[PDB]
Length: 48
Length: 241
Length: 98
Length: 48
Ligand SMILES: *[C@@H]1O[C@H](CO)[C@@H](O)[C@H](O)[C@H]1NC(C)=O
Ligand SMILES: *[C@@H]1O[C@H](CO)[C@@H](O)[C@H](O)[C@H]1NC(C)=O
Ligand SMILES: *[C@@H]1O[C@H](CO)[C@@H](O)[C@H](O)[C@H]1NC(C)=O
Picture 1 (tube, chains in turn brown, blue, green, orange):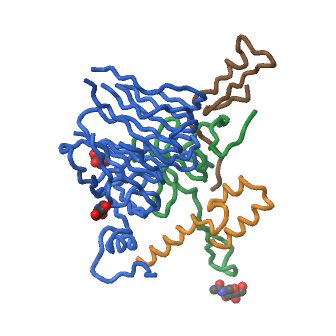
Picture 2 (tube, protein in one colour):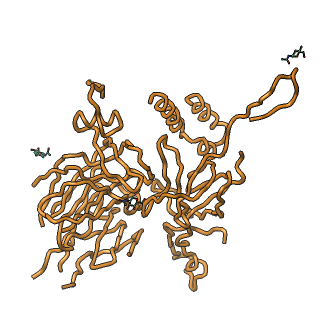
Picture 3 (cartoon, chains in turn green, yellow, orange, purple):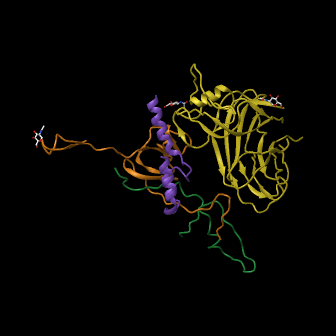
């Protein structure tokens, strides 16, 4: 018999690497003094 | 002081479930019948390839640990502690201050005095034992609880060390420290080496017995036959060089 | 600015899962564990946590789905040879197959 | 006993890489370009 179809299954989505305070933030910085906020262990949703 | 670690310090090499096969592995284990360097209730101890930490108390006086590679200044350093409740883990490169012994009523605040570019955070008659390993930037912890009645000796018996957590922090730990809760007005330590064992399983749960097949000739013979029972006869085990 | 260090990767993208299927020959992939076989619910319980059970001859035969924590069973997809039963070409041409 | 032991050490040999990258084919298949993965696949085929 042959495989009907291929399936992949992975655990739930954890903390979503908050980008709302980086893109949808209120006040940005000036060029000569720029922020360097670094992300860490989480899932990055580059599709959005 | 010194004592003998009879048959303690056995964890699960991996997460696989095995029904009843008597499986033989090869990993870093605490050798059977070795000295532990047990203390009283505490200098720095070298973290070579992993340690076995055990504690016997009746009151919640033993507290978390501090790890590192230089233990002086400006380097990556693990720091696991515990208050009255909600165990907090704080694992970052920073200027850790000293050895903050806890001072007891509930009024206990002497921990640290420095903060810098932290990289990780976490907020959440008995025998508690732990195993710490530093493999490929992963820090694995195994833990188990065991009720006891005598507290001046290390009890006899077997218990597997179910995995607790894992952390991806890349670090090369070399020494560590321990924390107590002395008032204001007994922990075991052992090292572990690459060995070979014959963990049992029982299809209804977990490991029930093991044999270190490098200790004595019967261990080697059992390890060869892959069974805990040996029948009368002569068995060729290994070579002598 | 993505960066690559000797430390293990921590920030990595999401993986799209799918609704599992039972009682069919499929290609499974559970957190890297792949292969094929018929998926069936188990009559056995692992532990408060275990990922995948093996057996003698170190074959993977029991896994748990990391959404409902339910242990499943892996059975190889049906295979076997076919045999031809014939009474002789001169006698007749009827054929039974096994 | 001998027949079962031989048939068991036969199927246990499937988890040996014979000096290749891995024992499983589906990982060396989807982790290398075909032209060099041919060498690994051949080196595993010979051992099996
Ligand atoms: C522990 O070391 C001492 C010497 O330092 C030795 O006499 C003793 O036999 C050792 N313990 C074991 C269990 O070998
Ligand atoms: C073994 O399994 C049975 C049910 O299959 C269960 O009743 C029993 O408690 C188990 N033994 C343990 C958990 O020691
Ligand atoms: C087989 O076929 C030949 C010619 O077709 C015939 O002479 C012979 O009797 C046959 N034998 C049997 C057993 O059918």
